[PDB]
Image (cartoon, rainbow over the protein chains, first blue to last red):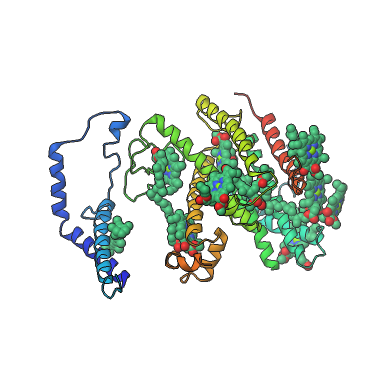
Length: 95
Length: 124
Length: 186
Length: 37
Ligand code: CLA
Ligand code: CLA
Ligand code: CLA
Ligand SMILES: CC1=C(/C=C/C(C)=C/C=C/C(C)=C/C=C/C=C(C)/C=C/C=C(C)/C=C/C2=C(C)CCCC2(C)C)C(C)(C)CCC1
């Protein structure tokens, strides 16, 4: 199989559904983590290491920041190589 | 007052100076540095190539002379920089200030070396 | 509203913009203790300063026809035996670095031997501080590029650039990562 | 062990005759011109 089509194709699908299908659902479940509350309430260096010091703002209308791009892109790459690797096993000698 | 004279006070002379990069206010010091550096850098290559110690070598004369012109521009850039450090330690034009002159010296180095390189390309 | 590494991203609070080259880039929030950020800021420059000299040295050695490649310099034998080089380096570097640290603790700035700051020529200003960091960061990225390009391509920095320029689409990271047997079999 | 390399003059003569003097003169010129606080 052509790696460029399969890997890019799978990544596009996983980015497309993530942006257009599961974005609303994913955000709602992320608020279920708000009900519990913040991890720590302190002002020491080690307490600062547990806070969202940097907020990744995005200009995308739906709020599809880079962290979401990395998450859904990784799944597409993972699925893409699974498809390629399995298809490679066809026509393998002594393997 | 001072002794009036056409050379000191003439219309044609005054207009010519007012258009030179040094006297053309409203331009960023860095840009003036590049404009001044290019002009001097281009000329600086001439004498080194024609009258240098390797002037009679067919092809090495161009390279050696220009490479020495580049060196002199580097030394001049140092002179400009340290002059600003000594002169401006504490007015109308931004150039005559510690911040302005430091930009001016940097532009001269960039413009001067570009002029030396541009002069070499003209030969070959 | 200074430029930030990510469009439309307000910089984090612990980054105030006072430091030279402060683009608000700290996704992991490593620098948030004022006692560590000051140490890291000094640590950024010294890594960059060594990188800047290293990149110039590798490029200079290649441009001047020095052999062998920069990653085989140690194997070559010089006037001084390799055993004698290390004790000399350890004593000299230990002295310079120890006094480098002592001055930093007292003054909080960077210098050489007994002078802090070390600015004999008087060139020093916020612009110069900014220019040092940006050129330093570029050298740090550049040096890693040399190391990895030596691993994959096994060509010296300038040599690799010429190959890319000669054949841009034919020669690139795509070609070398799929031709390790050919390049390493030579 | 002591013998320096055969190329030592090529580096040290320009270094001590053209480079260090330039830095030394720049250091001294800035120093003398420097104004007291
Ligand atoms: C800015 C420095 C720089 C520049 C100008 C070049 C230029 C070149 N590289 Mg090199 N390279 C660099 C950095 C650089 N490289 C780095 C950092 C690495 C390590 C990943 C490599 C690894 C590398 C390899 C393995 C190969 C090249 C090759 C090449 C040539 C073809 C271009 C290519 O394939 O690039 C595409 C691939 C790259 C890895 C280049 C990336 C360059 C960007 C600008 C780096 C950005 C870094 C970023 C700011 C870091 C953020 C960190 C984050 C955690 C915040 C070309 C001469 C190829 C060649 O023909 O060499 C002779 C080749 O085989 N480079
Ligand atoms: C004033 C006296 C004088 C003159 C004219 C020369 C001339 C020369 N010497 Mg000699 N030299 C002298 C004194 C002099 N020397 C002395 C006292 C010593 C002992 C320390 C030496 C030691 C010496 C050595 C060791 C060497 C020379 C060499 C040279 C040659 C190249 C110099 C060079 O690169 O200049 C570079 C020139 C410039 C950067 C510019 C010169 C000035 C320009 C032309 C002024 C133009 C002004 C312009 C007209 C104003 C216009 C204004 C308008 C726009 C309003 C040349 C033939 C070299 C050689 O190979 O000779 C064959 C060489 O190796 N000389
Ligand atoms: C120890 C001190 C010293 C040294 C090492 C030199 C060295 C040199 N002089 Mg002499 N000179 C000196 C003192 C010195 N001089 C003094 C005190 C005076 C006044 C009395 C003179 C007056 C003088 C004149 C009038 C002339 C020389 C020239 C020369 C060159 C003669 C050999 C040749 O053919 O070069 C050929 C040169 C080259 C092929 C290029 C060499 C490299 C250039 C000059 C610089 C490159 C810089 C680089 C690109 C960027 C910066 C690098 C740096 C940061 C490391 C040579 C570069 C001649 C010459 O050609 O000068 C340019 C010449 O005409 N000198
Ligand atoms: C702007 C814009 C746009 C566009 C966009 C784009 C084009 C994007 C892209 C994106 C992308 C393109 C992304 C990507 C990502 C990726 C990633 C994130 C990856 C990851 C990976 C991984 C993680 C891997 C792993 C692994 C390995 C390494 C080995 C083997 C195994 C595995 C596979 C697992 C649009 C028009 C739409 C809209 C408007 C705007």
